[PDB]
Amino acid sequence: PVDVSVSIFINKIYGVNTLEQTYKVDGYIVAQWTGKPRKTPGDKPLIVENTQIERWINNGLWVPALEFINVVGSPDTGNKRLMLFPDGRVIYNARFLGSFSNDMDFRLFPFDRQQFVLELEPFSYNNQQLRFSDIQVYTENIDNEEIDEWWIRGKASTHISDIRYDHLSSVQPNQNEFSRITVRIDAVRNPSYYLWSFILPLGLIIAASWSVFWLESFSERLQTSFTLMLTVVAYAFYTSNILPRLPYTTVIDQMIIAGYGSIFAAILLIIFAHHRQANGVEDDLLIQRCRLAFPLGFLAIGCVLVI
Amino acid sequence: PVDVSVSIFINKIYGVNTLEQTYKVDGYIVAQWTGKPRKTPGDKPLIVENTQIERWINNGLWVPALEFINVVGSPDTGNKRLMLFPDGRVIYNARFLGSFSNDMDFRLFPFDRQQFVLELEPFSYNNQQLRFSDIQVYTENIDNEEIDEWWIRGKASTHISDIRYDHLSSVQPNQNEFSRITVRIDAVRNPSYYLWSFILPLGLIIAASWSVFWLESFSERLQTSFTLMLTVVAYAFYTSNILPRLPYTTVIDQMIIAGYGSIFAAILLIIFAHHRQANGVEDDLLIQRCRLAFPLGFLAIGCVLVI
Amino acid sequence: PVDVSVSIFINKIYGVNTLEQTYKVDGYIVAQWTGKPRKTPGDKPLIVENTQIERWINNGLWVPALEFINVVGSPDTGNKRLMLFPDGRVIYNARFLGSFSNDMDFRLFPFDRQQFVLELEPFSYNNQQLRFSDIQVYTENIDNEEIDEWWIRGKASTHISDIRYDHLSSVQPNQNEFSRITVRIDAVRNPSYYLWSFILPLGLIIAASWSVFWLESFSERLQTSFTLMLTVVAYAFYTSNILPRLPYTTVIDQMIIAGYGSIFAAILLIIFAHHRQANGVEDDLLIQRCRLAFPLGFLAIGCVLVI
Amino acid sequence: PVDVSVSIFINKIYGVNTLEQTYKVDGYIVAQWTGKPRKTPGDKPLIVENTQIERWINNGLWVPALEFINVVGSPDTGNKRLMLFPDGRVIYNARFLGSFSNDMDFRLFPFDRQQFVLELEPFSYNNQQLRFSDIQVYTENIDNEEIDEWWIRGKASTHISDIRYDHLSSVQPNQNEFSRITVRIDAVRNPSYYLWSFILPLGLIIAASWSVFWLESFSERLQTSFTLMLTVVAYAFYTSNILPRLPYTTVIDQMIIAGYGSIFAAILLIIFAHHRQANGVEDDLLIQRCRLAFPLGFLAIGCVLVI
Amino acid sequence: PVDVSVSIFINKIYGVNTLEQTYKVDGYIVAQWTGKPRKTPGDKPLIVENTQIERWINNGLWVPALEFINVVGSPDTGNKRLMLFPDGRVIYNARFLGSFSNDMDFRLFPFDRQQFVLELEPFSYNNQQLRFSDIQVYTENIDNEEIDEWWIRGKASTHISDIRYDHLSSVQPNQNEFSRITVRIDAVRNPSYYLWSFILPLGLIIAASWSVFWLESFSERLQTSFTLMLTVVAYAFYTSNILPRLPYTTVIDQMIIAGYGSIFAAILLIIFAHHRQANGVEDDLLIQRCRLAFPLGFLAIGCVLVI
């Protein structure tokens, strides 16, 4: 197996789409191996630009095609360079831009912690023909920098593994294991924007929903509760286009359903308080001192869902 | 007819657009057949990378073009590989990414059950020249996994059929039947997000619309009903962009029209109750005890439309 | 002139954009003509796949370029096939996907009746060099089927005409007439979705706007009218993105302006009724019995605009 | 300098994006010049289709590259044709589709009057090598037709000018002037849709905002004014996505700010009227007869801003 | 090292996306250097159009590939020209259109001041093989012009630097420094649109929120405050799609949170004023004279956040 040494340089990470769970990565890839010796002009290495590698491959040069596994669409490749050394080593440097997809579990959505993953693998050559020696990821541009609301924390984790492909077993009987490289970059979401734009006004609106019990008219209590219900329905509008449709509920979604439940429970309590009239003369004194009990219970529920 | 054995490997299924009834499938296709024997370097099979298959096809190698029938746009093909064996068998391995379209009937929209279908067919060779022997679909990455709100349940169903094309009858008189492969993957939608985000708050709002009959002022009853009508009109806004424009009505659409009907019926009942004054002195006692009759009738209607 | 027989097969019609007046058509085109006799391998016809037609055209084969006239953008062509027969006839089969644009007049917008038109023409050869003999359109997949809200009714109308191009008169003095083929497919919009989602709730809201005259307080009448005005302003929001910006008004637009006029007229009538107080003591008895006159007049106006 | 005669035929103008100030133009371009005589098959002109012009250019034929100056992106070129005449004249006919950008000043936005401009220029040859003789624009399909809300009025104005490029002065010392052709098509926007959809309901809402002074309760006056303020805030929502973000204010924007000013001024007047109580007993008689003075002043202001 | 002189001409800057921090730049690039002397036809320079440079590069001509560093996606290149002079100098003129990304810090968002940056670098040749001599940027079309809300103020700053690349150290031991050119264009945002569309109506609405203390009914005060809370919640809707999700707060965002705080503080003050009843008889006289104290404090806070 030919030993190929890969070096991935990340120019920038951008376009992190949480709705589609994709992210755009731009960078360079440098794959270096050793072949048969050749005579270059002088002792200097020979540089072959893009659309001139085709002539050398037609002449019979072995240049493998290293594809990206977790990419969405054909990765937009830029310029490509081939350095041929007189001692025999061949270096392939290419510029890639790709939309890559990862798992991205959004349980703690504003306080999220994800990893951007690049998977690289030969398309045609198994580990009995091509083997990855080592990889160094030069993530120096985005080392500790803020790509939007994404603190790229730490360095890049590098892994070389072997993947047994089963659909190639019928065409390659006992040799269908491919060498793979995984690059993992740990990122933390910046929660500030959601903290001052989605969590704080919803909390104020839920407190204002608690404020319906300080009125002295049941009909005005219902009208106030319905206006605040309309306000909460006005929310979760521009919340639905900040995260995808997940089976589970996040902090902002729990706060939206908590506001709905608080408003419907306030409506139910005032309806039952007016229903509590035994003979049309009993007023509401014990049942409407929940101005300091309903917010206390809601704060206890919020503490339970937070922790 | 040359017997071609196809193996389709599905890397991921993503981008399931319910509005356009398309879905993006990425994977590999391995078509294997047998031709005339040839002399490769050594006894080892010869691997021909992408843009080097053109030279072999120009020399006269028979490589058929297997197209996708139900694809939307030209399928973005990645790397392609040609394994030539000394015994004579030729293997063509290609990476595809395509937007595929299927029927996708949305009667039970949150509790939906669809199938993703891949149709594969030779473009030029009929069943008297090319015949598909068998297909194995290696759907191991998405075997039991949750692509968004889509439980990929079960394995993949595989079918080989013959399609008689009639527009090719004039150019091919009695031989216009093409071998086709259909791959069907059964998927179930995850109903949780719609259950806690679209069905529960609409149900609470419809209950709050029932709550208008507990007031003691007809004018305030009308004002409350109009505010709740505005709230229901605020709904069906971000419901219209979750499913396409279908001729029939789904569960969420039936609940929206049921809320509209409940609010308009409440308005009609309170208008008729104030109209029920025979001489300006008759109040509303029998006609306004529908606080436990109107919700009961609505629950019966909801049970009828559910089952 | 070489006689070319064209056969167009429509796989599917999809993506009918009413806002841009475009629609995506996928299918196959089979152009058949007769040239000089040639010697193929055996007596069997020779099949030339895609990117192998270039060698035959370089050798000197006459293959015309049939373009689409009413297409938006370069039509995404898939695989192309060239059947060469020993008797001399040449057949060109290509797979196309194109965004085609038509007139699409939207006077009766929910109950609309349009036709999807495909125009095909040689790019370079006039009718003194290439002439279309006949066309058969094999619209069998979408014969009587429901592409979204579009009942494809009937068969396909086929026409061959001659178009005199004037910009080519200076370069071709008396021979600038090009043979053209027009394919017309009649389609009817499915009005059900708009009937239960845009027309019915607007009608209920306009009836609820009539319901303001049953109140017994002028100030509450104004407040109710302003809330219902806000509800109608909440409508025409997700109506503006279902059809383009047309100079004329459709049924839904007439209903929106009719709701605006009904609400403003109700406001004007209640303002004038309170203005009708001659000395501060005259109430409203004759002028506020329009609870059965204003809806009657609005229904008459709706009957006039419907028919 | 070689004299090149250009003829531009416009098939359709569509996709006029006011937000991005671009518009899509599809058509044909016919550039005709005269070179050295050549021997074609017979005395008939020789037609060279697309991807066969490359062989003739490789053999040494002079075919200039005429680019579009004001285009956005690479113009999608379709089929291209080369007519070679035995007398020596060469004709190049190409089909283009391009997104072109123009100035598009939107002062009178619904009653707008713009011009669509196509600029054409050789990429490499200055006026000492290539010179445009004359241009005829055959705008016969869109002569007097309604591309959406765009009355294409009149014919096309044609201009040939010389542009001195300064960045090419260092590489071409005294010869850096390029021949350019400008095509201008005058278009008028159809104001009907905005007239019945954006101007009329806003005017009705502003009249309804004047209608707050006919109430007999200051608190109800404030509540009514705040509801109408909410209605005006509901407007300018789907007005913000019909025109770009311009430094100046258009008619619809002036009407929106006029509605805001009318509502805030009504609030200020009723607040000052209740503040006008000298000792808690003075009512509002002189200050609240502005039901025919405030609308008169607003109509005067609207007449000033209209003319 | 070969000395390359670069001249960049900017045709237009457009499509400045603040949400994605990208901007589209269209222009020409002219790279001029000197090589070995060659014999052209006559003493005149030889012009090589696009897709004819490939033959000269195949013959062995040295044409470097100058890439853009801060570009998003492959830059759409148009026509390319190669001027070969008999004295030996080679000139490469290409037309580029690219989406370029810059930092773009949005602290003072309506009154913003950014710079559009173009970074240019050889892909393969270090400073021991290619060195940039000087660059002149001919920004004459957009010298003092208004690209949308972007006053392009001043001229273009030009810089030539050396960048040490570390991922190329293993393949190039002591020679991994690349010559780079940075072009910086200073631009100022036009604040007018936000001034009359987002800042002025929000300020009027906050003043109207101050106007709740002039009422004489606590229940009506709460209802008015909740309606105005709904109006502020209606704002920040079409504010969220004018700037990206930034960790910090801008002027418009501070005004939105200031309106939320003013409304919640007004609610809290009126609740506490009604709570201030010691024995059910004490009214509100001292605590409700904040009609000229609460606006004064809010104006002081606005002055603090402005400066």
Image: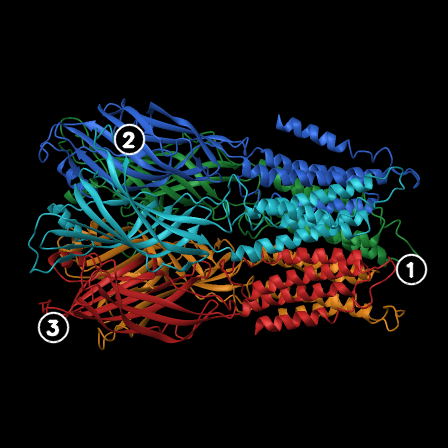
Chain colours: A red, B cyan, C blue, D green, E orange
Nearer to us in this view, D44 or A77? A77
Q: Secondary structure at mark 1?
A: loop
Which residue lies at the image location 84% right of the left edge and 38% below the top edge?
Answer: C273
* Distance from the alpha carbon under mark 2 to that under mark 3: 62 Å
Q: Is residue C244 above or below residue D238?
A: above
What x and y, as percent, mark residue E42?
A: 14, 49
Which residue lies at the image location 10% right of the left edge and 67% below the top edge?
Answer: A41
Q: Secondary structure at mark 2?
A: loop
Number of other residues with Cα within 10 Å of mark 3, as a class: few under 14, some 14 to 19, many 20 or more: some
Number of other residues with Cα within 10 Å of mark 1, as a class: few under 14, some 14 to 19, many 20 or more: few
Number of other residues with Cα within 10 Å of mark 2, as a class: few under 14, some 14 to 19, many 20 or more: some
What x and y, as percent, mark residue C30?
A: 26, 32
Which residue lies at the image location 29% right of the left edge and 59% below the top edge?
Answer: A78
Q: Secondary structure at mark 3?
A: loop
Q: Which residue is mark 2?
A: B166
Q: Which residue is mark 3?
A: A87
On the rendered structure, is B49 left or right of C109? left
Establish whether labels 1 and 2 are both on one chain. Answer: no
Nearer to us in this view, C45 or B263? B263
The amino acid type of the residue labelled 3 equals Asp
Q: Which residue is mark 1?
A: D280
* Distance from the alpha carbon under mark 1 to that under mark 3: 103 Å
* Distance from the alpha carbon under mark 1 to that under mark 2: 93 Å
Establish whether labels 1 and 3 are both on one chain. Answer: no
Q: Is residue A190 above or below residue D52?
A: below
Q: Are marks 2 and 3 in contact (CB under 8 Å)?
A: no
